[PDB]
Image (cartoon, coloured by chain):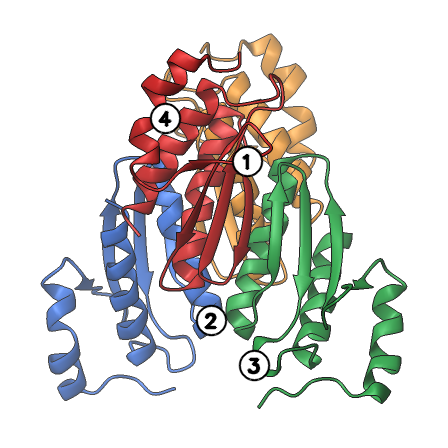
Chain colours: A orange, B green, C blue, D red
């Protein structure tokens, strides 16, 4: 795991920011809030992300209350954003649009 | 109190489901439909949403899963046959499937 | 439907406080942090609690990071602690046991 | 690769001891699991589902309320492989908890 270089960030983050992801101030990580119609959808969303988290062995820092899911992503190994976060974020977006 | 569907309600509620892929099970008063997804992640996400609803309604599917495929059979044990509960759960299952 | 009285709180929170649940200070709700060996167990735990949440139509406020799950419980309908919270927390403890 | 006669003798006994049996007419092992309710049955399935994705090896399973029937085999080698023994071992670990 290697923190994204300034060149990678300018190339990989814009598409994520365009759909709601934003970097945190005092931390090298990205965050996004998701709002579904109900819990059935929110948890179904979480279930699919959970499966991928185990496949990639990269887990989200997330909060849920009924239909809301807030997600923060960062790589512990390299203490900051890495391709893992970009990959999981992209996967998360794929799941979300179906919800 | 669950009660099996009469001939009238079957002719009014089943055609709608047949029109979307559900068939009546041969040799048993139940309906079934095979779902195919791109992968297991999708198939299990599908199962998770149906499972939540199953507990909400206290009506469970008889299903078989192998990677990206999920085969579902619906029937009501209480009345040994199809009831409005199966029609309702099938409708919900359809909603979730279409989203994927 | 209704917020717990003083008596109910004294008679219903013991088994819960004894296992780590504590009432928040700025709001009428109880909180507890759960720690599992890994995410597989942590999410398995969440999956069982999620099913019961839909069965009871009472959902938790929870934060998860790998093997840790922080849970806060309160009833929106009555703006505070109700038996729905006592019941779900009790169920949560039962599930936590099955998760190592 | 498909398990050899020797590997099966070294890896199946422990599983057969807890209820796993080889299918007749197909190179695969299967076991019926019974839980108190669906909440437990599906919780069990979710933990197994997570591991299935982590290992990229999936079970052939049937569920009806509190019952879960699992069949394991490896498509790639048309039969039992170490992947089946490993997943079955993980499944056992989860089941003893429910």
> Where residue C67 sits: x, y (%)?
31, 38
Q: Earlier in the sequence, mark 4 or mark 1?
A: 4
Q: Nearer the viewer, residue D57 or C14?
A: D57
Q: Nearer the viewer, residue D15 or B49?
A: D15
Distance from disc 3 to disc 2, alpha carbons, whole Å, reads 19 Å
Q: Residue at x 39, y 47 (%)?
A: C44
> Where residue B28 sits: x, y (%)?
72, 69
Residue at disc 1, secondary structure:
loop
Distance from disc 2 to disc 4, alpha carbons, whole Å, reads 39 Å
Is the residue marked by circle 4 packed among few (<14), some (14-19), or many (20+) residues within 10 Å? Answer: some
CB within 8 Å, label 2 to label 1: no
Q: Chain of mark 3?
A: B
Query: Residue extending furthest bottom?
Result: B1
User: Circle 3 sits on which residue?
Assistant: B78
Q: Which mark is residue D24?
A: 1
> Where residue D23 sits: x, y (%)?
52, 36
Residue D2 appearing in the image: yes
Distance from disc 4 to disc 1, alpha carbons, whole Å, reads 16 Å
The mark lying in front, picked from 3 and 1, is 1
User: Circle 4 sits on which residue?
Assistant: D12
Q: Residue at x 56, y 34 (%)?
A: A22
Lateral position of residue A9 relative to residue A27, left or right: right
Is the residue marked by circle 1 packed among few (<14), some (14-19), or many (20+) residues within 10 Å? Answer: few
Q: Which mark is residue C55?
A: 2
The vertical placement of C93 against A55, above or below, is below
Instruction: Say if labels 3 and 2 share a chain.
Output: no
Distance from disc 4 to disc 3, alpha carbons, whole Å, reads 40 Å
Distance from disc 3 to disc 1, alpha carbons, whole Å, reads 34 Å
Residue at disc 4, secondary structure:
loop
């Amino acid at each position: 795991a290697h923190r994204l270089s300034a060149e990678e960030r300018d190339q990989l983050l814009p598409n994520l920011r365009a759909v709601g992801w934003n970097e945190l101030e005092g931390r090298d990580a990205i965050f996004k809030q998701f709002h579904f119609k109900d819990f059935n959808r929110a948890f179904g969303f979480m279930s699919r992300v959970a499966l991928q988290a185990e496949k990639l062995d990269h887990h989200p820092e997330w909060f849920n209350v009924y239909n809301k899911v807030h997600i923060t992503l960062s790589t512990h190994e390299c203490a900051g954003l890495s391709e893992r976060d970009i990959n999981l974020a992209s996967f998360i977006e794929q799941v979300a649009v179906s919800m």
